[PDB]
Image (cartoon, rainbow, N blue to C red; front, side, top):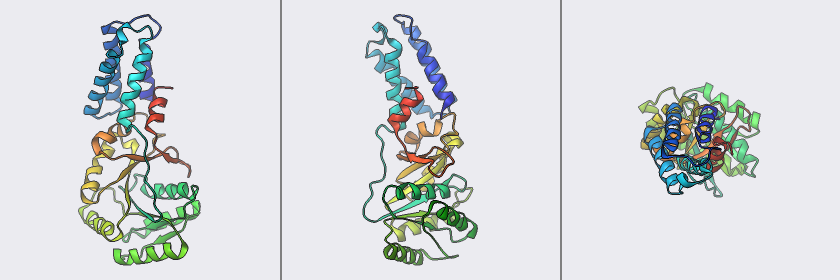
Length: 294
């Protein structure tokens, strides 16, 4: 992922390698390429500025201009700027005995499938998850998950058309109790665009169900724009974390690098492939190093 960005960053940094001490201009030439690289990867402007700013200052502060291995110093400062942009330290929801999570996002963002892959992931971690297809208007949506549930071997309770949250809560709580499901994953309704009506019902569903986490699923491929919807969902519902899908298909990386600044929400998981196991915890340090070819 981020093949373009990765290559460029490494090419800019290498210009300072194997040629003795470098000058301020040698350093600046490289810094410009880094900037240009971030800009071409659809990276948030403030993020890109801060990025390059600390790379230069931290590098200078490490006497990079008197270093015999300047490129190595720069590689280290770039890694740190990258680590910050991606979230610093990795994090995942803290699970309790009873967990109920909301998977929110636009239709086509990978939301429904993520629900299933997430169910499979924790299932393999010793949890007894229960998928809940919360779309009360579209029977098609509910069927998609139903099919996904059997594919990953996890029960799927389907809400009835026009079912009230109160009724939904009752049937869901009952099934979980009688079947001993400790992780309840609710796939909320999704539409190609954010529509005030649904958002209002969504807020009520949260109100009635009291989710422990609210995961906003985003299509990393849509670049920086993917982050646009974030504020809407958080202001009306309340997002606790992010999930970027199709990272293996993203050559830029603008969304993953900008997520933090734009949404202020942590990226819990990442969609690394179309396979059912193509969902894994997001590791900022690991990803920072991989981009820099370490």
